[PDB]
Amino acid sequence: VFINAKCRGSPECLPKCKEAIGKAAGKCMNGKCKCYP
Image (cartoon, rainbow, N blue to C red; front, side, top):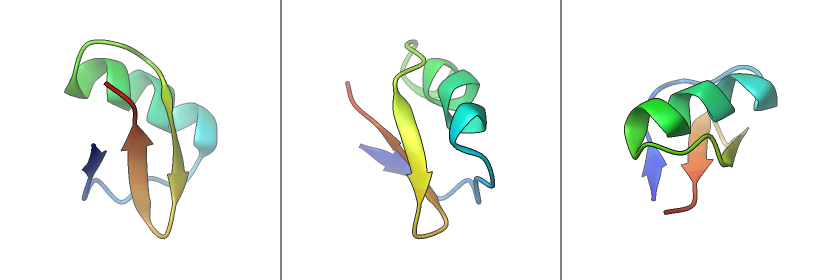
């Protein structure tokens, strides 16, 4: 799933995804985070 959190750095989406679902696996594109459950 993704989050509206306006991400600005690919490496920033890692700590975010981990804080979103629990794992730091995802990227940042289209102004959104792409975390994979």
